[PDB]
Length: 330
Image (cartoon, rainbow, N blue to C red; front, top):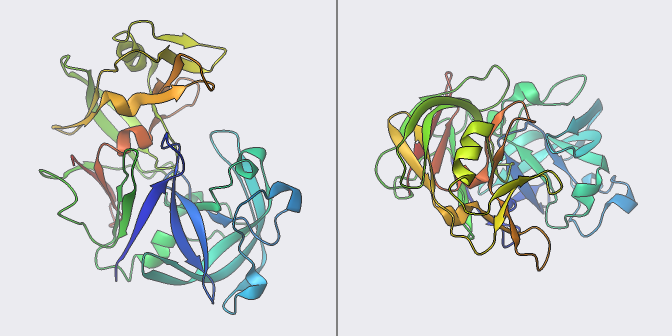
């Protein structure tokens, strides 16, 4: 089987992308943030504290004839950005882009942190990291991809995120018309539960490529590109007036500046992030200080190839017995 769904930016900055997901019978369609950095499929629901719901579409298990409470199971998750959610668990039928999984664990939120409440466009998350990170207790649950992968024509999914435009998540096939050139595959470590890989280096603008190993994770649920402070400093040094601001929480630059591109290595191949993808706009409405899309990872513990990086590529998440990642230009 295969599936194919369009993913749409939630705002003019590409701060996140939402993909419609059909849950239950009759279908309830919720717009979920596909997140290759986590492993829980959780949703706003009829069980979420009413004061913590503000415009989201909710899943109501009682209205689904295929929903079944997963007796005793609870979940609680805290994300790298300090947000969190928790609740109980149903199994139900879940379909993405025509691909259907029966018995999928659908984590119903009873509580969500403020950042989720305040974002009316995201109705939950669909984790696509490895199932070892799933938070359901006492019986850990499988991700949608893990449940689907036996049925898929090929055990893969692809992320083709758009720059200021919709893109595509495909399951079970590689759309050879969606990219240019060839796909370069690179090794993945699953030891932390992430799509963790090692970039071969970087270049800033038209500068020379620096060969150096940069271990990091491919994370569709992170907006920005977080890299070691040495790399980030080398990038912003090429932007006149750019500076790291403790008050704002990272590198800012004059909105009048033209940003250089940033290149990252995938084996012997190179992915070029155009400079315009690194512009996240004014730090506050009307300000002439703009927020940079490449930031330091020093205070994270891990480098993160977020959407700024991934949207410059056609990315293959190969879930074969020995997983790999593939990157092509597009």
